[PDB]
Image (cartoon, helix red, strand yellow):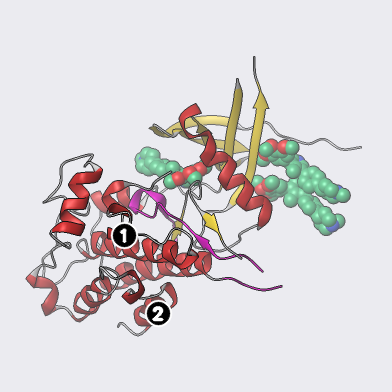
Amino acid sequence: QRTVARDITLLECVGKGRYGEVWRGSWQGENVAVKIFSSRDEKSWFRETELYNTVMLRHENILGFIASDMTSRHSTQLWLITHYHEMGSLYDYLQLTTLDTVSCLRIVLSIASGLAHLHIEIFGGKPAIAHRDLKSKNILVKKNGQCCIADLGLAVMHSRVGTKRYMAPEVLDETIQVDCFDSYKRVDIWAFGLVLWEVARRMVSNGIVEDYKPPFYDVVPNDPSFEDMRKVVCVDQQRPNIPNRWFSDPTLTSLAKLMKECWYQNPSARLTALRIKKTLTKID
Ligand SMILES: COc1cc(-c2cncc(-c3ccc(C4CCN(C)CC4)cc3)c2C)cc(OC)c1OC
Ligand SMILES: COc1cc(-c2cncc(-c3ccc(C4CCN(C)CC4)cc3)c2C)cc(OC)c1OC
Ligand SMILES: COc1cc(-c2cncc(-c3ccc(C4CCN(C)CC4)cc3)c2C)cc(OC)c1OC
């Protein structure tokens, strides 16, 4: 009656970590990305699969789902198959690329667009979703200059912990209102503000650019501890540095104001993803 072609050729490993591996693969002549989960990270496969079984997200700034596959061995093998973005992660891309005003805005507005789509409840639709591990390694760069948000393995739907370097103060001081879905959107907005700082540093103005650095590179070690982060973010209330050169450039001046309004200690004071979008559409 019909052939179901399920073979995926694994061509090259583009990522290896505690999570497992990501591979460029081929299905029927077409590139796909294949995430092979470690035993350590099986719950991330279950959570993303449960979310996509609930709502088939389709958005230009969300990594495109193709399949969740569980295969029996004499162990269980868990694969997540998605769209493949050959330019790789935003983290990767910013190491070896500076930006002009148009490319910087296009990147950050595309991320805000993806994030607002996750956050919003649509009736008749989708449940509201918080990502809970937003960071530059979880954003991919598309050939058209927009990005897409990846990895919903920690996501929570309305209707474990994130990466410590990107944790909001209420996560680090354990005051987060855990019974309140809006709390998790506000944790994402904090992390978005850090990503906006990472990108803005790489935007050239008046012949000046900053080197790529991760948030808090100047105040915490590599693989900072929970306490290292708590001391910086909660006790001392430090925030990433805004260089003087930004204040000569109208775009970077506007982006500095936006990132400050993602970093309020009081989570309810932070901008919403929809307000960030609107502000970004009025810049330049
Ligand atoms: C099981 O596994 C995998 C399958 C596929 C795949 C390959 N060819 C055809 C299909 C297909 C889609 C949809 C229908 C419909 C048609 C209408 N009818 C009333 C209900 C069913 C049939 C067949 C699929 C889904 C790819 C995979 O990887 C990319 C798979 O592995 C994860
Ligand atoms: C998982 O992913 C991919 C799957 C496929 C694919 C292969 N066979 C058949 C299908 C299909 C056909 C028909 C319906 C509907 C149409 C209306 N009504 C009759 C109900 C059934 C659904 C599904 C698809 C979508 C192709 C892909 O790429 C070209 C995929 O992406 C990698
Ligand atoms: C963050 O998370 C996920 C990401 C992906 C994913 C999708 N497209 C492309 C990639 C990628 C491709 C290529 C490079 C490099 C290779 C060498 N080159 C010279 C520079 C670029 C890096 C990254 C990835 C890693 C898929 C996922 O799941 C299937 C992810 O998990 C949800």
* Foreground residue among 198 and 257: 257
* Foreground residue among 115 and 102: 115
Residue 7: image quadrant is top right
| In this picture, residue 161 sits left or right of residue 157 | left
Disc 2, ligand 3: is the CB inside 8 Å?
no
Quarter of the image that includes the N terminus: top right
**Residue 170: which numbered mark, if any?**
1
What residue sits 18% from the left and 46% below the top? 228
**Dot 2 amino acid type:** Arg
Give the alpha-carbon distance from disc 1 to disc 2, as whole Å.
Answer: 22 Å
**Residue 275: which numbered mark, if any?**
2
Q: Closer to the camera: disc 1 or disc 2? A: 1
Mark 1 neighbour class, 10 Å CA radius: few under 14, some 14 to 19, many 20 or more: some
Task: Based on the picture, tell me whether residue 141 belongs to the magenta stretch.
Answer: yes
**Dot 1 amino acid type:** Glu
> Residue 281, how many percent across, how many down?
38, 81
Range of magenta residues: 121-144
> Residue 211, how many percent across, how many down?
15, 54
Marks 1 and 2, the one that precedes in the sequence: 1
* Foreground residue among 185 and 202: 185
What residue sits 65% from the left and 32% below the top? 70
**Residue 15: which numbered mark, if any?**
none
> Residue 235, how many percent across, how many down?
16, 57
> Residue 213, how many percent across, how many down?
19, 52
Quarter of the image that includes the C terminus: bottom left
| In this picture, residue 269 sits left or right of residue 245 | right
Residue 197: image quadrant is bottom left
